[PDB]
Amino acid sequence: AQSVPWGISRVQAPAAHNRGLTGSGVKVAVLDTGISTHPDLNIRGGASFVPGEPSTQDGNGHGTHVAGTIAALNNSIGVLGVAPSAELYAVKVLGASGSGSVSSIAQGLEWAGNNGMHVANLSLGSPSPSATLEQAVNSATSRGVLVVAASGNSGAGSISYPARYANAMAVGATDQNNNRASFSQYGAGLDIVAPGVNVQSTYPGSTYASLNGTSMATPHVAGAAALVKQKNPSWSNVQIRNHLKNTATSLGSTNLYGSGLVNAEAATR
Ligand SMILES: [Ca+2]
Ligand code: NA
Image (cartoon, rainbow, N blue to C red; front, side, top):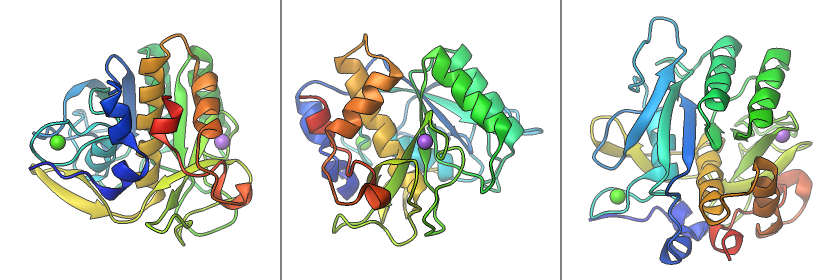
């Protein structure tokens, strides 16, 4: 039996699927700890930029979980992604510890741009500015990638990097009451929010796990971007980003929420 995680329903992804919008033909790079093969995922390709970690398999779990929020297959098992037909690419930029380097993240962004990705999901952050990260985000954006990044889990009123940079779409986390999760970073640069508390998704070992974080919110938005791109194949990164914001459900102050809760149904009307 397939379960629909609450956040997938909350972003109204099933309604989009009922329109026939699934993310088919849309290339989504997951810049993370890898993606492990799983009965509820299809992985089309990828690359590793972690020294000494040559494979794209996930030695952590984080990247596999993020990937399932984007694209868990629509079937009789497991969970269900926002964009269950998206073409997933495992871009390993974080090691098994859950951390990476600017170098590695930047290389993954460069790979996404050079491989024609439509969306790059960055469920990751660094506390300090990094001109190398800024330039890699700008380069990927120039090449046509929509970069979507987590705001961070410190609870502070400023957001992590690279989310803080203008060309990364910054995603914070909400809870089941549609309030900002306590940990969700906010402030200048926040674009949008999505479910990030008690998010069930795929995990290595052909299993499932529930996690909290802005890392879990981010892939809901990446998946919604894929639905919009399937409907509107001519649209740029910027057009997609703006449409997601314009069709979000306002939750209050933009300082706390950006444009509010992403809404895949509204975004694909
Ligand atoms: Ca499934
Ligand atoms: Na940003």
